[PDB]
Amino acid sequence: ALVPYAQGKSIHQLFEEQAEAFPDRVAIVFENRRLSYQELNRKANQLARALLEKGVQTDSIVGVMMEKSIENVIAILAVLKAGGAYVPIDIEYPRDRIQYILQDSQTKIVLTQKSVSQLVHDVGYSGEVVVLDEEQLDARETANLHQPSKPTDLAYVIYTSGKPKGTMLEHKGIANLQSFFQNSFGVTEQDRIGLFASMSFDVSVSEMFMALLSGASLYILSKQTIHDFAAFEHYLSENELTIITLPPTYLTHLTPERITSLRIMITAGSASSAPLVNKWKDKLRYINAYGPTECLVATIWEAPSNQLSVQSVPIGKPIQNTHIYIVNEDLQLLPTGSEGELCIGGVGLARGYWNRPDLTAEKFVDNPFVPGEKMYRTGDLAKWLTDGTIEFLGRI
Ligand SMILES: C#CCOc1ccc([C@@H](N)CC(=O)NS(=O)(=O)OC[C@H]2O[C@@H](n3cnc4c(N)ncnc43)[C@H](O)[C@@H]2O)cc1
């Protein structure tokens, strides 16, 4: 790779390495409960062995219908360790949408919990249902499994909206992001990282593995904490959280003077205004992160430090091992200042859309610039600036 990363390693392999180096460090926090890296890893291994016994294997797609919680993360890690990929199904989606995802994904096994069992019943799911807080796992072996794995194996299928489509992401993209987070944000095991997004929104993937592939601690925010801006600020300050990713629409309601310990604020998913950036960029490192679900994150713009106010907010430059092409309708490259479609190549590109071969071929085209690879057509309008940053301009 152009930029070094842990090539050849799976997500759970990278997590296991952190658990070996930082066994007694806090890995995950939810309300009054927490687990160390060693405890989290052992519990994930016990559940992974149960999942293997039930038949989970390479490119098994496993539904997860759970409340955000420590146990939710145990389940994700266990699916990966068993060799499968997870499909997160937010339990607050409407019943019609849950049923569509279950049917489209063709998953034969759904991981849930006692408080969600009735919803699994009421959506009519006829596959295998594992109620995790009814399974007896404590007696199972806790060592790592070392199942066969390749970086090109599926890691997760996340649905977006035509009809919702299951976007298929492999391990390699997240391995590259481990290296990106450590190089570009300087993430270390000392960091304390909040988890804000729904597990059905791929921001949550970034947040979870930003912590757990670096030895840092992951603080899963409760619904009560998110629902009250003052409670959110108090939680971040009392727990001395150092990194958080937010929608700009949430950030606009927060008070910088009430957050004590953040060193990085990332916004993602929509544009931040220049006045919002100006309000935060001198209190901490403000980062605008852009990307489609089809590659998680594609570009970032960190507001340059110790500079006067900005009047606009670029989406920045491609992250490591990722390439941006701004092209016309004939996929020809445009010069600086010309508006065109933002297209993406790189190690984090999705495999495509689950059981949508024509749509996949339409959106993941042959990369004209790198023979043998694919390039994703985002439908986003953009242009280059002469300083080499990109301006997001809306939809084509
Ligand atoms: C470090 C770190 C993690 O960083 C990220 C960054 C982006 C993502 C996205 N995958 C989140 C997202 O919104 N995905 S989405 O599929 O629901 O929507 C993608 C579209 O949203 C818009 N978008 C998306 N980020 C922007 C933007 N920063 N400005 C302005 N429009 C945007 C563009 O239209 C994208 O094509 C996740 C993690």
Image (cartoon, grey):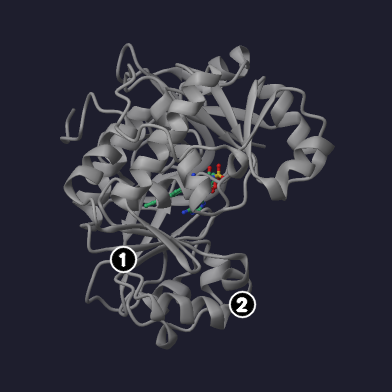
User: Which mark lies nearer to you, 2 or 1?
Assistant: 2
Q: Residue at x 73, y 42 (%)?
A: 117
Q: Specify the amino acid type for callout 2.
A: Asp
Task: Examine the rendering and report whether any part of residue 295 can be seen.
Answer: no
- Left or right: residue 256 versus residue 250 is left
Q: Residue at x 28, y 36 (%)?
A: 176
Residue 149, located in which quarter of the rendered image? top left
Residue position for label 2 = 228
- Left or right: residue 113 versus residue 291 is right
Say what secondary structure mark 1 lies in. loop
Instruction: Depth check: give the residue in front, 115 or 157.
Output: 115
User: Residue 330 appears at what percent x and percent y?
Assistant: 48, 22
Quarter of the image with the C terminus in it: top right
Q: Residue at x 67, y 19 (%)?
A: 106
Q: Which mark is residue 303?
A: 1
User: Residue 246 appears at what percent x and percent y?
Assistant: 49, 62
Say what secondary structure mark 2 lies in. loop
Say few, some or many: other residues with alpha carbon within 10 Å of mark 2 (under 14 / 14 to 19 / 20 or more): few
